[PDB]
Image (cartoon, grey):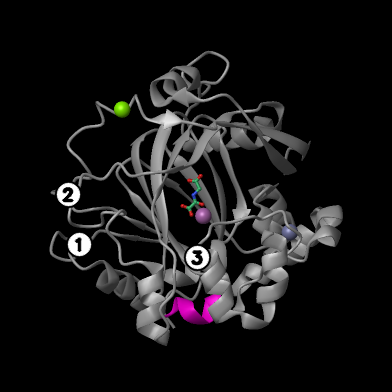
Amino acid sequence: AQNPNCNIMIFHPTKEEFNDFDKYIAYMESQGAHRAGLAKIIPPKEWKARETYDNISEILIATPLQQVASGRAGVFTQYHKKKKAMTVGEYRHLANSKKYQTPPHQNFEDLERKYWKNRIYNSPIYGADISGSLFDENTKQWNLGHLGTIQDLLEKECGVVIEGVNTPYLYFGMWKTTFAWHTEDMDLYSINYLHLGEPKTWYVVPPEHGQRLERLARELFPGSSRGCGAFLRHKVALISPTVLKENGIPFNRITQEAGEFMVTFPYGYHAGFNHGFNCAEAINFATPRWIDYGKMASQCSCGEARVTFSMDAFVRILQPERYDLWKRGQD
Ligand SMILES: O=C(O)CNC(=O)C(=O)O
Ligand SMILES: [Mg+2]
Ligand code: NI
Ligand SMILES: [Zn+2]
């Protein structure tokens, strides 16, 4: 078995190898990359996502989210308070203000220490989940707005035609902005490109050990666990690496820098934080290997998780027994 310790693997495709996206994902899996739950892909040196980022400031962040924490430094939840709209140029200025900017630090490890010590005492503002793309239309390789759609994959594998669309999302971050522990909708893959700015640190649990993380989360968030049998679908819970290590949960960590892709694999729990002002683009995708994970994915039916239009068909076809209850949660 390849990669039996479930380490995060880093790949350096050549420009020739960067042509066929599906083929390269299958290659990485042949080497055991999925066992970690997360992989880094450094694009060939010839490749670019677009010519410059000089003209992005007029993008609108319609609903910036202030991420307010509750709990203790290593075990907390966050809720999202909606803020008034602002442009990316306004948000960048905010991120660089004395109240919100990255503190002085020695290196990524020192910054990580400061994040876990101090996150809860601040409420950073995250320009998350913005439909759109920063890939130039002429970028033909690994253009996250030109991927094969999940609906087309389901149709190719299973023969059933379904409604729905699959488009990317932009994330504008600042120091301490945080993504809570989660897997993707329907335990899909994700791919994330860091277009510009400061780094993003990731934590990940191998898919084969995801239920260990879920059992710890039930213990640490006991009222949330009584409320919902899949409350990590709410995307609000944080658990630090120190707490994971104290409880024997297998995980790994890595820092993504501008110009790099990350892939999350089906049922790979992940969480993390931004180092400073940045912009990422991410989208879900599927492969034939996903189908079995989609059929087995947990679902929130308490009503809190509320997701896209396109998830309806995935539940209806892959999980017909669950469909009725899940849809009640959606409506
Ligand atoms: O970048 C973020 O805030 C969150 N991204 C992801 O969870 C992902 O790409 O799967
Ligand atoms: Mg603009
Ligand atoms: Ni994700
Ligand atoms: Zn729920």
In the picture, the disc for residue 18 is 1
Q: Are marks 2 and 1 in contact (CB under 8 Å)?
A: yes
| Quadrant location of the C terminus in the rendered image | bottom right
Residue 60 figure quarter? top left
Percent across and percent down for residue 247 are 74, 59
Percent across and percent down for residue 65 are 59, 33
Percent across and percent down for residue 55 are 26, 26
Residue at image point 41% right, 51% down: 282
Mark 3 vs ligand 3: CB below 8 Å: no
Q: Which residues are magenta?
A: 288-295
Taking the image as drawn, is residue 283 in sight? yes
Q: CA distance from mark 3 to mark 1?
A: 21 Å
Q: Is residue 168 left or right of 213 when viewed as pictured? A: left
Q: Residues within 10 Å of mark 1 (few under 14, many from 20)?
A: some
Q: Residue furthest top?
A: 98
Q: Which residue is mark 2?
A: 47
Overall secondary structure of the magenta section: helix
Where disc 1 sits, the SS reads loop
Please tell me which residue lies in front, 23 or 2: 23
Q: Is residue 186 above or below residue 303?
A: below
Taking the image as drawn, is residue 206 in sight? no
Residue 268 figure quarter? bottom right
Please tell me which residue lies in front, 313 or 208: 313
Which numbered disc, 2 or 3, marks the residue that appears first in the sequence?
Answer: 3
Q: CA distance from mark 2 to mark 3?
A: 25 Å
Which numbered disc, 2 or 1, marks the residue that appears first in the sequence?
Answer: 1
Q: Which residue is mark 3?
A: 37
Which numbered disc, 3 or 1, marks the residue that appears first in the sequence?
Answer: 1
